Amino acid sequence: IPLLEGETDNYDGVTVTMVEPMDSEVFTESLRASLSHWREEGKKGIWIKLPLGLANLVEAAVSEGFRYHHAEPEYLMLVSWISETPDTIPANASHVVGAGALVINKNTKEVLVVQVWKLPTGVINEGEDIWTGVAREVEEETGIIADFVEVLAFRQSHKAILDMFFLCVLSPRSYDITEQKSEILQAKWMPIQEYVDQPWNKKNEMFKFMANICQKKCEEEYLGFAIVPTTTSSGKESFIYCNADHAKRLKVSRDQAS
Amino acid sequence: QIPLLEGETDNYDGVTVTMVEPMDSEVFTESLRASLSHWREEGKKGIWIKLPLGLANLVEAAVSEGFRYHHAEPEYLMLVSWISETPDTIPANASHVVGAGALVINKNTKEVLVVQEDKNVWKLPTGVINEGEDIWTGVAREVEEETGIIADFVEVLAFRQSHKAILKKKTDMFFLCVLSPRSYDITEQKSEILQAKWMPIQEYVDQPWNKKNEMFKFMANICQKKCEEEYLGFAIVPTTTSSGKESFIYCNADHAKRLKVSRDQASASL
Image (cartoon, rainbow over all chains, first blue to last red; front, top):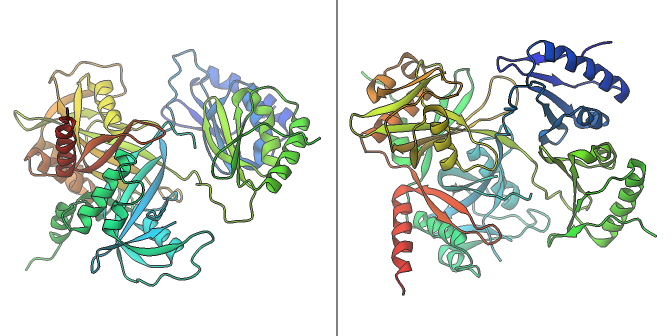
């Protein structure tokens, strides 16, 4: 009876990417055989990637002692330690990234707010850059276009019942908000002092600190992190967010001699 | 009779169902379809089903009714479905792998802790930051686990988003951090690294790979500048949010110093 196709690594593990439908009775028996031939071989650490359409398989896997590792929509990652060596299966090291947009009209010291008023926030997609992501959210929410300047602050949060947050400052290229930009979304330009003094004022130390940081950048006294564009070991893009002045110094220093 | 699943109601027109007892999958289907209908009428927007590992016989049933995976811990699967006509509000679980590097400076002779295990012979101590784990705690953990050295987090010098090995839409997240060492004695560790030593910053910088490609050249340059005590990064100031009370904001180190000064000098209100 046939084994499962497994792809190996130099951590002694194996990841089975389940791609085509299969009867559950067949899967458990084909898995039980595979578990036997993996304990004889390099034994420890087996991963089953189970896509949403193959949800008819998760019980079969779990019944065989697999547990959950992490999930995206359209795939579930399951894992098992099949060695008698101490279970050292690494926990998930992926995080959900969100971004907060501070869009400053530097001319009027005013900021773009949304539905009581808040900064436009969203999440950074898989494969998306923070600087790209934060701008898209502004455009999706208010219709206005704005370029990314700096990252003012970031934070983490949990107990997570339902994450990483980057506060970014954006520079607007347009000022007209469109009606109606989104369903149950509403927007206006607000003076910075009104935003800081808003009904939360002293609600908690965290919102108050983030607001004060927003204000210091509105007064042009806050040095955040700016981007230095670069490339990885492959041809692929990369961006270093570092001290704004050093970011300039590094970016400027890229020019041509006599 | 509507077989209605017990759920808890949030304030954003959502219901969370936590399944705790075994249920026949057919019965669950019937009960879930009924529930989804009542909720739709009741005005509910986001429906969350939390299925423990041992109740995995229900997973397919939930999925069949339009539920998709949201989050999984070893012991449970959290599933979501949006049942309202309005635009879907739930955050997608779009994740990035998160890493940290430790620049551990010996302030006496401008040396840093290095290990042999990116394509440098001697890299900084680096690892992944677990989901749920503070960067400032995780980077220090990696130091201890690899070298035995107890080191304190001072600043985030830089963070990096890369796109990955032609595979797909994926992007990395990596935090370079600077840490102050308590001891200078490297103990042999039950760890994947082959060896660690102290290495003069200049020799680390002048390594072929750090000289060869631009990205590591910039990271290495940042590290060298912080050794010259001329780099300002993002330091930490701790806060409390309302519902969970343990939180950290990484912000400009001079502002972090100012906010900490003002808060400490505000405790004097006695």
